[PDB]
Image 1 (cartoon, rainbow over the protein chains, first blue to last red):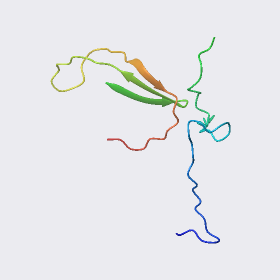
Image 2 (cartoon, rainbow over the protein chains, first blue to last red):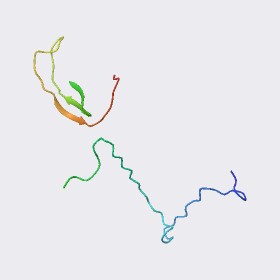
Image 3 (cartoon, rainbow over the protein chains, first blue to last red):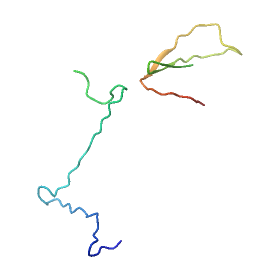
Image 4 (tube, rainbow over the protein chains, first blue to last red):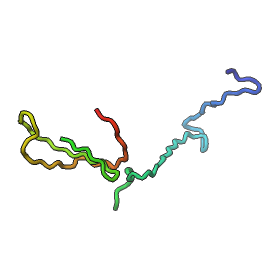
Length: 48
Length: 49
């Protein structure tokens, strides 16, 4: 459990600051996983 | 009153509320039961309580 010559911590802490430039910013990612079972569809916009 | 039906992958549960006053048995009257909820759920319920 101690970092050595061939051992390092897998969980590098994120160094998010308000001013860090493009690329190092925190990026909120939402993955919506939709399933299409033979039951009717429930969540979407109304029909026009 | 409840009617538990399951036809064609659809669970139909009707509702009826009645003020009742009879002593022992089912009354001599008529009542339809109106749908409150329809549920398109395929379940093979085997026990209840």
